[PDB]
Image 1 (tube, helix red, strand yellow):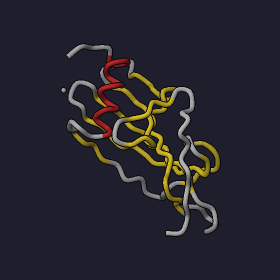
Image 2: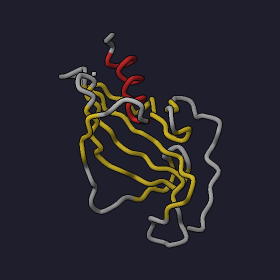
Image 3: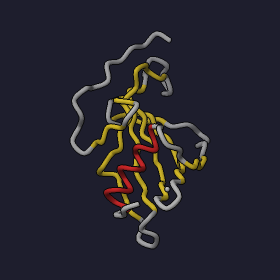
Image 4: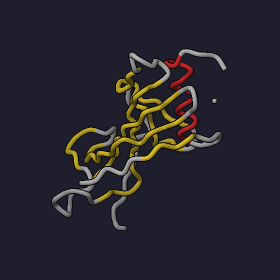
Length: 132
């Protein structure tokens, strides 16, 4: 409960800030468009935290950001959460920690939500189409 962070307001080059959360970003550099099915795009979402998470071996060390590996299908807006890593610096960098079991799931995105904005942006620029 105790710890308290000031997430950067200035945005690191290549990070795309999303609607509805000024601390949630797409790491533009991490984007991989699948060779076999170009509608499928892999990317990291990166969240700068408001409150430190004590997820490290040593209980005084806390994370400042989270990096999450996503896979997006631009044809049906399915978004799979693949893995989560915690970092002790902002922008998903620095000393890393992670859960033993990674909890995975796929959603079908819905309008007016943070990750839907991500998909509109990614698909518009990397899915390369005009048009769900």
